[PDB]
Image: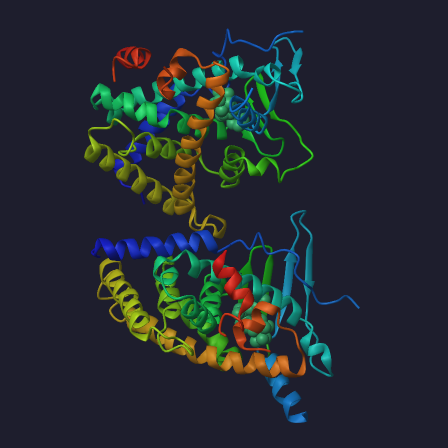
Length: 294
Length: 288
Ligand SMILES: O=S(=O)(c1ccc(F)cc1)C1(c2ccc(C(O)(C(F)(F)F)C(F)(F)F)cc2)CCCC1
């Protein structure tokens, strides 16, 4: 079956996932909520509306007491209203990014890298590890991310179905969920994406590339030992292609975030560091979180 | 894994091409036809042509329901053709997957369009059989195609007479890995001697490379000397597959003659009534 070194690798990543992924979102508190009650620059606004409306969600908050608060966003009719969920979205993103930083911090193979390379791997993979973790709480039947007492529900349109799948970020979630991956497979995907030698500012290419290869081999070997079903043929290569697709979604998402941020600033200071909104000097929060213990 | 990095990348490209284009669970095979619920020498040969490849059909609904179809026992008549429209839809679905497979390969993509057509015309049936072998259950004599199953008619060991059936039992017995099946598909796809091929030298060179990669994969990844002649056994299976292919084309053409059933894509692949002009659907599918 799997080697002892492989069984230890899976155990360590799994232990790190459980210690740093709060799946019930119990500690997600003090977040902002939406309120109770030219030429050429108009083309920027045209793209920003396309960027936002495709990612449109309604928010549900179930109280411990049994009560339910529901927020339905406004339909697109002008400016300012389209940005109502952004402060909340930035807060959820920030809480998720902090969990991802903690995940990387507990892993010995990441801990033993120079601080600058820790910053560069985190900068390069944060969104990717966030999407992987969010996929585990995605309900593909209801088009809803189920975050404990918080729920994010995809806004139903006249297009589909077919219209929602036109958004690569949404299609990724349905395509990844269809694979019915195990916790071990998701965690090995996070490890693969985290240890990418080709991220900007990475100096220790060889060490990172060698760590990535062993996570990839461990994944292939895990699949071979646990997936004999004819449903799971080529599962390893499907996962690898999904990771390649996630890297592409990531590049598109960064450019999309900058466009929204350019006309409507919303990004938190941690988000501005990870996304490059204006190495140890330009990433103060990251450096501090990395110096702190877990 | 004692292969060249090139050889390792050649396998990776074929494996990638296979995962992208082989719907192993047949989940996208939908909207197919089903048998309804309701000169003399030509008809004599056609009866012999169909009777041997007789199958029952099983369809398992997601709800748990089972629909089963048993074919008629000759007697007439046009009833011997009851499963052809379904079969034409299944082959057409398989053929589209084979075209997509070939399209993702750099070695194939880099060849002139006319040669892409000629290779696809020559190898389509062969690559389909190779993929069907992977879903073949030699114990139950059934091709397990997701929610569909094609079960061989127990008439009445006598199946071994039909070369198309003997092929599936013999190939299955070799217990090949995915990598070996995909290298088999490449060897068959890149056949230089196919009718209408121009670049014989280039195609021959590519085939030899795939064969050497297959040979090397076997030496390095299989317990030697138990698998001493596995490469040669695979090469004999391919030779037998080529003769099965020539026979199957003649068989399909005889059936078509007296009972037209082939879809437009099948008509182009098999030569049923300027290489781009005589293969319009294929050209479109390769240009997409
Ligand atoms: O390849 S199979 O395992 C296959 C399986 C399901 C399936 F639906 C189409 C193909 C199988 C077979 C191959 C070709 C043909 C036909 O080509 C022929 F009748 F014209 F010869 C056609 F498809 F036209 F009917 C019929 C049956 C079935 C049994 C022998 C091999």
